[PDB]
Length: 422
Image 1 (cartoon, rainbow, N blue to C red):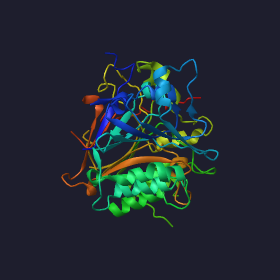
Image 2: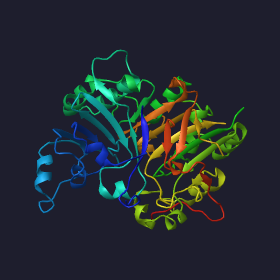
Image 3: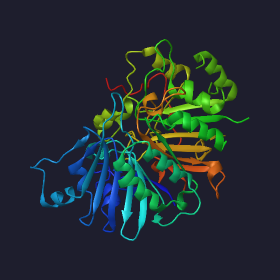
Image 4: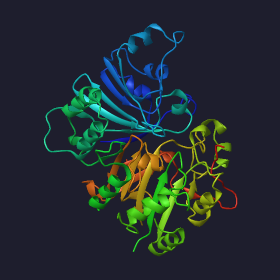
């Protein structure tokens, strides 16, 4: 079936787990189709086997590093001629942020992966990274419609590029998606001809359809206020109020929300590295460059999240492995639990490229500006399960596995601060 794996690192595993080499190094690999935010071609192309026939690369113009002549070698020169580039020119303040791998094998088989890392050496090896791996698919006529397939095809169509239509989508269309009939493909696109991001996801959650309500987000960046005049966070003031029914599509005052959360027993979580977690990371601040929360300008926004919603959670120092310590992860997860043993059984879980920003998600009235993509596990969509099951990789079969500890621990309000890259 589909499985989450923890990306091996050159630093953390010196002498379950996956490498780009496992994904691309297979002798039976015929073609890869790739989507990423950043490409370091000499890092990436060394991952492949000589047998590969085609590598179609979808990327943002200006993010594909070519190989320098002095870095070239005869092997790489061979793989380079197999590469086809599809460059997307993004508007300002917009990112092609999707990570996606579509592999085609000798015998007509297909496999899809959603790695959390971009295809660069340092980002791959320094922060913790995960990879979602699809079950094995086969080129073959299709039976019944598969929501995952249909959504993927919508997503591909939303680029409005002939190269994607012809080189990618036609190929995807030939694959039978039956093994993915339980799961959902959730995406953001800037296309105005296709609904996506938060608005679409909210609607999907409504359609798919007292206790404490836990809502957890793990994100590598945290956006600023949705509003210039008031402190309003995407997770606390919009997404959670929508998911819970506190609000419906046509933002509440902070204090109203705080009373609503108390009355409905809503618990918000955001997992983001503390300043101190870098001290107890084995490569120290080496992975810190990829964790962006710029809260020194509007301090009351930070304090509202930290003190009023008490939203921030950190790793359990007692549960982490020696070799990885408290190194943060660049994966993103959004999950809901309805109840220590919290998050082991979920109502739903989204694993995605999308960070907690309005640029990734859009709002009710604004479309996303990014391309993003992820996979949704929902309890009401499974067959042989009641809930989505989830475990931590820190203890290493469940539906989902996460790089953070379970449980996560509240920030100590006397001591802990969110890592501020400034």
